Each structure stands twice: as C-alpha cells, then as structure tokens.
Length: 459
Ligand SMILES: CN1CCN(C(=O)c2ccc(F)c(F)c2)CC1
Ligand SMILES: [Zn+2]
Ligand SMILES: [Zn+2]
Ligand SMILES: [Zn+2]
Image 1 (spheres, rainbow, N blue to C red):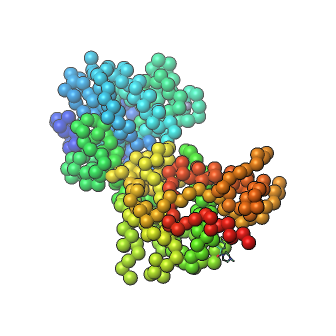
Image 2: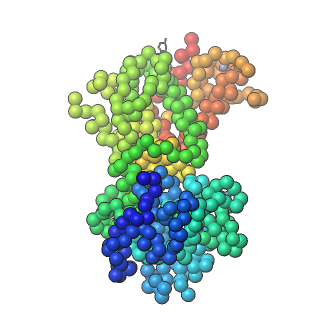
Image 3: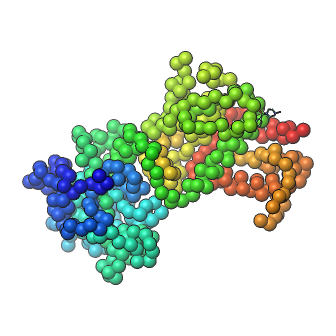
C-alpha cells in the first residue's frame, strides 16, 4: 500500500450532470481511459494520475485547485480556473482572460504552473471538486508516460514540448506546451454531503463565490487544506528543504534566548510561565527565575481563548512574573508577556495560503496557523531590535569596519568603543533577527520593557 490502486472505485455521482449516463460502477483505470489517456501496463513510476489523501498531504506544496466551468464542451467555450486566481477561456474552434484556442491556452498553463511551483515542489497536484468538464479538458493540456528527468537538469520532468520533443522541470520549461505527468485528487471522493460552497462556507468566511471558475478552485484547495491540516493534524510528516528553513529555525532559537534573557535581566521577574509546546526546554538555562511549563499544542483552527488556557482553577497566579508565549497563538495576550506570533499574511515559499485567513507554514512540518490579528497585542508593544551581551571582550581566532550603534548593549559600547568580537556577534545577531522577521515572525513585549535597564547589568 504505497500508491492509489487504479482498480479502486470512484464515485461518479458528482460527474453525472456534465456527463449524463455515466456508469455508477467505475474504477480509476476506467475513468483515466474515459478521459482519453492510455496507461499501457507501464511500471515506470507513474502508476495512477490520481493519488491518495496521504500522498496529497505529503505533497501539499504542489496543490493547485482546478475547476472548469461551461461558458456555453466541443461546441462551447470553457472557463479554466486555478487557485492562483487565474481564469483562462479556451475555445474549441480574479484575472479574467478572453477566449483563445487550446494551443495558446496550454502554453499559458505551463508558464503559470512553472512560476507558481518551481520554488515549492517537484510536481503539481490538481485539487478537484470533480463534476466532469475538468477531467475531460485535461487531454487538451496534459501528456502522460513514464517518469522522466529534465533535459537541462537532474530534476523530475513536469513539462513537455511538442516543438522540440523534449521534457523539462518547473525551472527550465520556458516555451513548453504540455503539463507532463500531473497528479490529481477529487475532494468529492472524501464523503461530503452537499455542494462545494456549503461545505467550504462551514469553515471559511474569507473566500467568496463570485460565480467564476477560479473562485471554486480556491474554495476546493481551501476545503482540502481544512480537512488535511486544520481538523486533522499530522506533525510526524517531514517535508523537504526548499529555502532558508535551517537559518530561520536557528535565528528563532537565538532571538528567543536573547529576548528572554534580557527581560529576566532588566526586570528580574521571580517566576516565568512558559505556555506552549509540551516539548519545550528552558531557553535561558542560567537564569535564577522559577521556570514553570504549561503544555498547549499549536492551534490550527482558532486562536486559544486566554480564559481557557489560564482560568478554571501551576502557580495559578499568572499575573505574577512574566508569561512566555513562543508561538502559542492566543486571542489576547496578558499585559506581562513575551510573545512570538507568526504573521500569516507574510509572502514566502514556506507560507502557503490557508483556511479562513489562516496560513499553512511548512518548515520541516506543516503548521496551519490561525489568521494574524493585530487586536491580540493590545496590552503589549512591538519589541524593538537590540543586541545584548555580557560575554568578555576578547577576539580569539573576516575583516573589520568600526561598529557604532545605540542598540549594541555591551560593556565595550558602554565604555564608548565596541570591541571586534561584539561587533562580529552584533552583525551576526542582526542578520539572524532580520531572517526571522522576514520569515513572518513578529515579536511583542510588555509595555514596561526598556533596554536602558540593561546597561546597569555592568557594574
Ligand atoms: C547576580 N545574578 C543573579 C540573578 N541573575 C539571573 O537570574 C540571571 C542570570 C543569567 C541570565 F541570563 C538571566 F536572564 C538571569 C543575574 C544576576
Ligand atoms: Zn530542469
Ligand atoms: Zn476558504
Ligand atoms: Zn566587547
């Protein structure tokens, strides 16, 4: 049990308005044949165009919702909608493109998928709420065969060109006209009562139905994300390295140590309530503070209500000392907090669009995060950048330009001249900090926080 068997049954009830008279009894093997594709008993890495829910989850980065709406098909033009917001009109002769023949529509489809996916995945997964026209339109822009490699590199082939008889990955497909060996999954096979809008609208109020094909495509991928990452959570699945994952995670650990250590030095709280990951470890092991842990897994649906995380009868007096919410998404943080909250609006290769304003952050594991809400931070302020160090000024062991900065909180800067060691360390920390902020993380602190209070930790 690795791939989806072609002899698995496919419910055809969702297809019978576009395809009247369709057999109730149907397998993937028969459906693929009906779509105009011949699989030829091929044992070459592509056993089925359709995939299991588990395989779709492992390839979430490849997901592109796809819907085809009859404009008037063979006699009628088709509207092709994608979860990128694109709408193309194909003639058989929110981006709305006028009616053009399939030979130019297919070139645009290869361009769009390659630009959307080259930095995310090695394939495309067409996410459907299948009614008929999308499955029968695939023959016009999809070619299938054995698994192949790119003509310009070692990556797997995702495109094909009839002009040159060659294959390409998403990075080298300029001028290619066919999508090669795409994958697909029909959300209607998952057991749903009612149409797409009624099921989507149960969990999401951000995507509307402007009665256009790309709207349905967006709603379909959104519903597929809710089922696989919001109401079902599997944090065991590992995902490939596609960007700055390692630098981002390292920066987050450095920033956490720095910020918490400085808060403990400046305000000397007697107790720290660490609320979040049940696997968390003391980020400042040398601090005198009474460190107390509270377990709460990452919320994927709605942000935690502070009343449920805290109240209902632990020091119990969460008002005493400071609360650390490191990636613990709550509706309204208490005033005595140190907070790291992922901004779901961030544009990046790690952050995929999610359900109800939320986003799916994929860095080693998939974490659907609830919508970023500025009101959660009303009792706090934005934590300003600063670098603090009590380590000795000693070079040991990269050229130099004298560093001058009001945010380099060290003994050497206090004594009017930053040493080479704290200047290298300051610049490295500033880079780690910028990496974290650019990845989408936002830092928030109690209003009494003042880096001026750190200078006296040097006597
Ligand atoms: C005389 N000491 C005792 C109390 N003290 C700490 O508790 C402390 C140590 C290291 C840290 F990183 C930190 F955040 C806090 C610093 C001053
Ligand atoms: Zn290539
Ligand atoms: Zn939605
Ligand atoms: Zn120094």
